Length: 115
Length: 116
Length: 116
Length: 115
Image (spheres, rainbow over the protein chains, first blue to last red):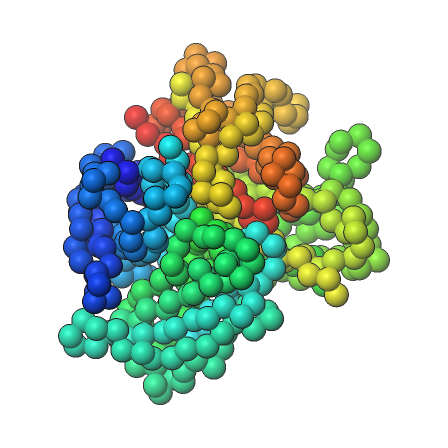
């Protein structure tokens, strides 16, 4: 599993559970092709999105549905979602972990890429 | 200015200067219509993007072109850009300041929304 | 002002108002001597802490009293405070702006350092 | 292990390895008593700092030696270190994970507290 997502709730100090995540791949016509998706687990994680075979070089977009998450908690949020757009490059480490720390009016994301 | 952007460079401890920013507004067909664009100043600030009159209700996307910024500094960063997508002015006119703090493999964005 | 602090509330999307800030400077015995204090304004800003003359070389600690801030909003936060410790003016006088973005279980701080 | 630390390098997009971490406990006389310490692993983690028996309620300080980390990489940093000060409370979740994302002139820290 070369692509992982770890989402944290900076308000409650807990993993962000049941957050919808959609991954897209940029197509030849510059549109976003659905690639993979899921809901974060009780540990705020989402793995098994793709395989080494399928995760070829290219531009990918990871959309985290933060708005629905905050609405479920009864908290008015700012963003429609958090977007993480990046290029997968074979000439570097294999495993991509996208960290995302969520607050109603702020989010931070950090990519950790390793072997 | 109802729409403002403040960008900081967390590697150099300075405002992020000459960063290109493109703003889009969602149309009916889910496509992103260009709304406004500019580049950050020496203070990492970008005002004069729009006016209260033109900045109507809608879903807006503020795209900060961080990749170019880092490459010019000799750094190969992770993200293509930093995207900030939000509904604006749905409860009346508001003033928005989008803060962004950039690192090659990380960014944070915080929105300050005030009622004039 | 050579020392400035800008604090934002990432839960409400606003400046963090009336946040107490204490600045200390390290002495010889590793103890923290009180240097200056204040509270953030409506803009989440705090200037007038010190002067160029008084702000000599040294190791400074900017302590932001976030716990009190969150408790007053009905939130029980994780941190006692947000501490920002740094060497200042060791290469001559500089201007420092300490940005802080607060959430109940998280905070970020970014320093902008400029040469006047 | 009720206390864990996960440190990430936001410049290189990798765990922050070999970062010294010192944990202190606030004593009756308001001074900081050394409690535990170590160096982050190849995964930027530091566990086995303490036990449930020893990790009683009280105020703790986690000092991350970020200055030495950046100096090793030949990068001039701003902070002397990153400090995370908090109260351990029995009336909540047991495991504390302190996340820290490091940049030369910025750091973010997020606490994740779970069962």
